[PDB]
Amino acid sequence: GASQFFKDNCNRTTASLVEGVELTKYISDINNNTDGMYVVSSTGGVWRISRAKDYPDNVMTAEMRKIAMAAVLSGMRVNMCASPASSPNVIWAIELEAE
Amino acid sequence: GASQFFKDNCNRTTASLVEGVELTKYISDINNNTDGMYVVSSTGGVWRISRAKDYPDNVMTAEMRKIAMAAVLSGMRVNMCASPASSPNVIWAIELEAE
Amino acid sequence: GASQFFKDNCNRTTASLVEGVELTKYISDINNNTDGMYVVSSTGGVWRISRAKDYPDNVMTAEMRKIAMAAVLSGMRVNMCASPASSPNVIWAIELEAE
Amino acid sequence: GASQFFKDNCNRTTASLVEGVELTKYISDINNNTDGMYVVSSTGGVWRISRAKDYPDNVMTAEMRKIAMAAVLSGMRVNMCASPASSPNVIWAIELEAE
Amino acid sequence: GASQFFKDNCNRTTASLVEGVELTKYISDINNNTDGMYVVSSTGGVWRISRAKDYPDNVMTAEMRKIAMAAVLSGMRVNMCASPASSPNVIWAIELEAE
């Protein structure tokens, strides 16, 4: 489940905390309208991974992409801090968990 | 099979949707007349991977290459949104599926 | 245990050595007040990974991220040289340990 | 075996087609006149991996290094389009095969 | 042990050949006087991985880090061309072996 750190850091934002998600699809799309990176959960949820060109969020967002692909390949679950009202929703924090 | 999101997104374009493709070869070529990144399926179909030097699509196309190689290395299948307006067809979106 | 080298180099700083830690979560966060990369141990301790924009520390901190993610995915333990001057404590050195 | 596509593209070059090669060593060297990336086959052949500073071949050559490393670590075979009469030979195209 | 190519290339320098090293720790350190990337063997020896800011040695030094981490993670041995001038000795060339 979500570490207390992660939980605490999400609640103080107007985002929703999603725990123990299994990601089953990883999407790269450069079509004009959908241009971006997406993940889909086992339950059919869809999320957009945040993007950023400038330091330092270009680092965090790169790692988000690494975490998402690692979850899909290995079946490890993730916890997410994501916007609560949109389709697809956007990821603002993600936590890869071994246990 | 392809997620609904992925399906929906490809259906809005001139491109066609290819599902359940097993990629078995990954190619990098720097000969000027055939320069490019390609993948080959178990049936011998060929696709070119999109490239881009500018942000943000240089990010998405880097992720397409990562997805392509992951699929070849692990046998995991992919869903593609490919444009038939070039030989080989060009990948505009790709979906890695565990499930 | 930490190598002699690591041990000795951490001793000559104002930070503390943490040995044989099992990392079980890896976090990327772009929320306003939490912006960064974090790791969580099997014992619920939390650390911030250092970051740097310019050469050569950009290389070192990139490797810290690769090491931390490798530890989470493989169960390999780490040794850390962390400064407790911040909360969460910040990693100044990290040692991946296998065989 | 080399895909038909890969064969045809090397067929249209001045190179040699090298099939079913097992790569067993991966080398990085920064010494003055031997500097470069090289691979060695199970039977002792040596090839230099092409390098390039400029887009788009900087992308292709990075992918060639990734394919080389993957073949070494996983024992997967590669097909090459390479110079035939030097030592080391240079690789102009490489195909990673799961098949 | 080392390929003959690797041996021949090291022997043209002031550096020394070290063979069949099993690396067991991988270190990233940004502390002021110990700022760099290091590896430690099963035998307890320590080496510094070369760093480079500009093309083309930034490519080769990036590959050295990749090789070093792979060795630690997989237990695969390396051969190194290392200069005894500095302490710890500096890796100028490295060869990952599979077979």
Image (cartoon, coloured by chain):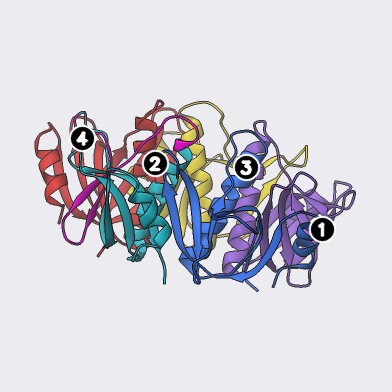
Chain colours: A yellow, B purple, C red, D blue, E cyan
Q: Quadrant of residue E77?
A: bottom left
Are circles 4 and 1 on residues that touch, CB within 8 Å?
Answer: no
Q: Which residue is mark 4?
A: E34
Q: Nearer the viewer, mark 1 or mark 3?
A: 3
Residue B24 or residue E96, whichever sits in front? E96
Q: Quote the CA–CA distance across marks 4 and 2.
A: 24 Å
**E96 vs C67: above or below:** below
Label 4 to label 1, Cα distance in Å? 53 Å
x, y percent for residue A59: 47, 35
Camera-near label (4 vs 2) is: 2
Q: Position of residue B44 (x, y in %)?
A: 78, 69
How far, Cα to Cα, is label 3 from label 4?
33 Å
Q: Quadrant of residue A33?
A: top right
Q: CA distance from mark 2 to mark 1?
A: 49 Å
Q: Are marks 4 and 2 in contact (CB under 8 Å)?
A: no
What amino acid is at disc 4? Thr
Q: Which residue is mark 2?
A: D31
In the rendered structure, find residue B17 and report the number of the disc placed on it.
1
